[PDB]
Image 1 (tube, rainbow, N blue to C red):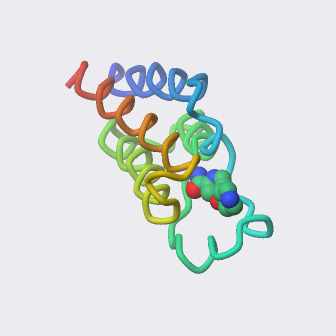
Image 2 (cartoon, helix red, strand yellow; image 1 turned 90 degrees about the vertical axis):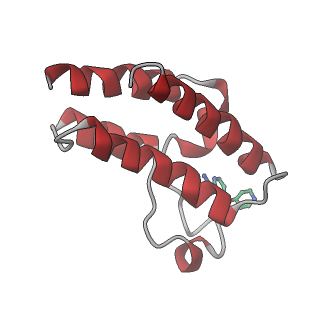
Length: 104
Ligand SMILES: NC(=O)c1cc(OC2CCNCC2)ccn1
């Protein structure tokens, strides 16, 4: 309900300020990341999710979690599990999955 979206605000704020958030704060600039345009067919990042959440672009917490899990699916698609970005994506994905279950 109304709490459906105040939930997402808590988690997105906590993800935005997380230590391991840096690879996901703003969209990937494909000019600087070769191959990213070819490989990732639906880029997503925390700032895009913030924009959408601010303008009411989510009708439920489900669609919010869809965008979050898309951030981490793209991360694992593009980065090796032992790359620096990959390690941060695993730390972030486990955080998100945890906090998400601590409400639902
Ligand atoms: N969130 C991401 O997927 C992501 C990928 C990325 O690619 C870079 C990673 C470092 N070496 C060159 C390519 C850089 C930042 N972030």
